[PDB]
Length: 213
DNA sequence: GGGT
Image (cartoon, rainbow, N blue to C red):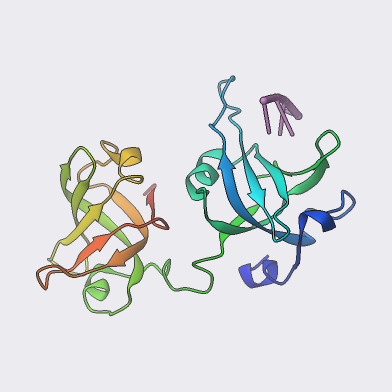
């Protein structure tokens, strides 16, 4: 089930998909050309769908019925991904890929083979020259604005606080969801320098997860 | 399961 095992699987174009293939016997490369809203009727059964384009400029509908929130945040129009674990299913004269089991994988092609999500420590972060990294740190200061959140994060390997800037797209979904002294994973941020003090910044690939501890 |  390793990532490298999943990337092993044969890549297929829309014209090659068959209903009789096992959901995990292939992987599909797709460019997101359209992303719907999340739909919600019931106390908890949200869905959404995207339109993905392949290398023949053909387009196919992908529906997501589980792990909806995470996947909705991952998928951005314009980006290329590998999708693994979807059921090829008939869609009225068409085929579609249907993601229902919550063990499917959406792998962004761009960050493929990078240490961006390597999850190091603040004192380390403040020492290492990577440009993309991830910290499990604690929020000790919050300056929240119209379009931008400035944080100061700290950890137990230093007495220094790290400065973190969060920009439009990702900040909206976080404007007042930060708690002081709570613990968060800052995945795939951008090491950067202003005043020979080192800001972390987010970009299109960044994510944030609240350590449940 | 569900459905644009």
